[PDB]
Structures are given as C-alpha cells and as structure tokens.
C-alpha cells in the first residue's frame, strides 16, 4: 500500500491496487524501472508495460505478458511478484544481474484490464476481453486466439458467444494490436513469454499447424531445463512440448505469432495447479507459485543472453 515493501504479495489485488503498485515501484527505483503506456483498452483503461533497464539504446529485449485471460488470477499475482523481484535481485544475484546489464525486460502484468475489472465486479470466471458489436448480444473475444497466426483456423471459435471466440479479424482487439505494434516497432525482442493458467505446462510453437518449428531441438532442450529448475523448489511437475502435440490444436495464439516474427525463444507457461482448484487457486499458493516460476523463466533468460 504505502511502499512496495509494504504491499501484500500473498493476496489477490484489484486493478487500481496493481496500477498503484506500479507507480510506487517506479518511484522507488527510477533508475531501473519505467512505466510505459502502449495503449488503451476497449473500455478506455490505460494498458501499461513496466520496462526494466540498466541503459543502452534499443538493447535486445525479453517480453513477458500475464493476464491475457482475466480469470487466471494467479498470473497477474505472479506478475506483481516478478516486478518486485527484478528490483531486489539486480546486484545481488549474479545471474540475473548479468541479464539486466545487457538486456531489457518488458513486463505486461495486466494484459486484459477490462476483463480483469469485470472478474472483480461481476463474474469471477470471465476470461475474454469486453469488446462488443453488432450481430451479437454476446461480448468479448478470447485474446489468445486473436493473433495473426493461423488466424481463424481450427482451434478457435467463429461464434461470438463462444468462450474461445477468435474475433472479427486478426488483431481486432486493441489489447492485442497494442502489443503487436509495440513489439514490431521495437524490433529487437529476442524472447517472448506468455503466462497463463492452469495445467502446469511449458509449451513452444506451434499450436495452429502440425508442422514442426526448425528450432525444435533447441527449444525442447531449453524447455526441459527450465522445467527441471522450476521443479527444484517444491517439486511441482510440468510437462513440456509443442502446443498442438501437448494440448490440442489452437489457432491465433501469441507465441505462434511471435515466433513467426523471428522471435526464437517463444514459450507459454500454464501455471498451477492441475485441477484441484483450477482458476480459483488459494492465495496461500501465490508466493510458492511465483518463486518456482521465476526459476523457470530465469533459466530461459540465461539461455537467451547466451545465444
């Protein structure tokens, strides 16, 4: 509340609390972190990214997004913990220090603010954005099906009332298009990570086509290693593989888009648990979840800095 050291990380927060947290963090570490507004949501809420940097101009960067699906509260909660962690570990953790000294990290805690607000205000289990239209009384698009990657292919719904509705056209949702333009304009992203929940999976592309990516052996080995690191803390077991072989066909996904943009290290994490609580994971699981995912992510960043 008054300081990031006083913020309660072991609990779930509303949108305004998370946005206040960002300003506080910026205030305390003006030299490391900045807040950028890359757009406004459908209902007009600002869309913010925190930039963590030790300088340089256009350094190679790491993108991380959380909360694209609003009801996955463990993701926004993990995001706020990561933001604090970066500031704590810079200069104490040799590894993470080496990463920040040469690369920038861009963190989008609440990718879908309108749906997050709605999860607190009206329906805890809403997952889509809140865009509306004409030929339907139904609202919203599944933002992870709106990217320009096999857009409209099998693995998405064409019905507006579906929970997996892909939208009118690729990039129709402003929350997605804001990310697209920002990443394209930067052009120096080397890693793209999207965090969702639940199922305990670490996936790589693709989900829209059975075709194998050419970087399959390396991605798989990085995935393996990351999973091994994650499990190391609490023994949480993840499986890993390409989206389509692992889950099922799904089109218009984030990481398929990023990888096709030339961003090699593109992975999606599906956090705890495996179904016992599902979207409604207990607040007592926030910290342990965050701590173990951090080891997973750090592992991918380390490989990135190195390759």
Image: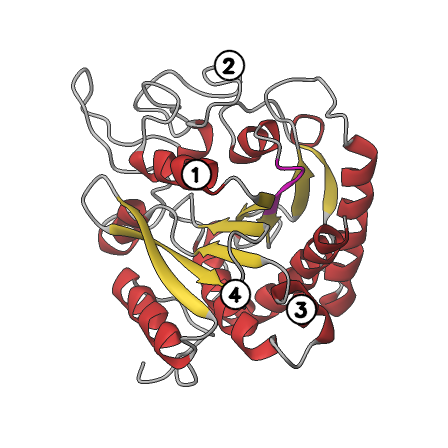
Q: Which residue bears the numbered disc 4?
A: 55
Is disc 2 placed on a helix, strand or loop?
A: loop
Residue in the image at 32% along x and 18% along y: 168
Q: Is disc 4 surrounded by few (<14), some (14 to 19) or many (20+) residues within 10 Å?
A: some
Residue 153's label in the rendered image is 2
Alpha carbons under labels 1 and 2: distance apart: 27 Å
Residue 197's label in the rendered image is none
Q: Which residue bears the numbered disc 3?
A: 96
Pointer 4 and pointer 2: residues touching (CB < 8 Å)?
no
- Give x and y (percent) for residue 64: 52, 51
Residue in the image at 74% along x and 44% along y: 239
Is disc 3 placed on a helix, strand or loop?
A: helix
- Give x and y (percent) for residue 59: 57, 54
Overall secondary structure of the magenta stretch?
strand
- Give x and y (percent) for residue 174: 30, 35
- Disc on the earlier residue, 1 or 2: 2
Residue 109 quadrant: bottom left
Residue 267 inside the magenta-drawn segment: yes
Viewed as shown, does residue 125 lie left or right of 216?
left
Residue 268 inside the magenta-drawn segment: yes
Pointer 4 and pointer 1: residues touching (CB < 8 Å)?
no
- Disc on the earlier residue, 3 or 1: 3
Residue in the image at 46% along x and 34% along y: 144
Alpha carbons under labels 2 and 3: distance apart: 39 Å
- Give x and y (percent) for residue 141: 34, 30
Alpha carbons under labels 4 and 1: distance apart: 19 Å
Badge nearest the viewer, 3 or 4: 4
Q: Which residue bears the numbered disc 1?
A: 185
């Amino acid at each position: 509340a008054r300081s990031t050291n006083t913020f309660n990380y072991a609990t779930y927060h509303t949108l305004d609390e998370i946005y206040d947290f960002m300003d506080l963090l910026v205030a305390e570490h003006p030299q490391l972190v900045s807040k950028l507004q890359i757009g406004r949501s459908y209902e007009g809420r600002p869309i913010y990214v925190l930039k963590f940097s030790t300088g340089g101009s256009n350094r190679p960067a790491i993108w991380i997004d959380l909360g694209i699906h609003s009801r996955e509260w463990i993701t926004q909660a993990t995001g706020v913990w990561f933001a604090k962690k970066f500031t704590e570990d810079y200069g104490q953790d040799p590894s993470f220090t080496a990463i920040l000294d040469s690369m920038d990290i861009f963190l989008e805690i609440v990718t879908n603010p309108d749906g997050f607000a709605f999860t607190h205000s009206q329906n805890r289990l809403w997952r889509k954005t809140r865009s509306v239209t004409s030929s339907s009384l139904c609202v919203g698009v599944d933002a992870n099906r709106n990217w320009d990657a096999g857009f409209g292919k099998a693995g998405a719904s064409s019905s507006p009332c579906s929970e997996t509705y892909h939208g009118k056209y690729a990039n129709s949702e402003v929350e997605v298009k804001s990310i697209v333009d920002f990443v394209k304009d930067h052009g120096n992203f080397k890693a793209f990570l999207s965090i969702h929940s639940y199922s305990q999976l670490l996936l790589y592309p693709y989900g829209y086509t059975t075709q194998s990516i050419p970087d399959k052996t390396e991605l798989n080995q990085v995935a393996k290693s990351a999973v091994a690191a994650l499990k190391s803390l609490y023994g949480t077991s993840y499986k890993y593989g390409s989206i389509i072989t692992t889950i099922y066909q799904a089109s218009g996904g984030s990481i398929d888009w990023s990888y096709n943009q030339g961003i090699k290290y593109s992975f999606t994490f599906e956090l705890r648990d495996t179904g016992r609580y599902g979207f409604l994971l207990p607040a007592s699981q926030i910290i342990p979840t965050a701590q173990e995912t951090w080891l997973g992510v750090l592992t991918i960043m380390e490989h990135t800095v190195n390759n």
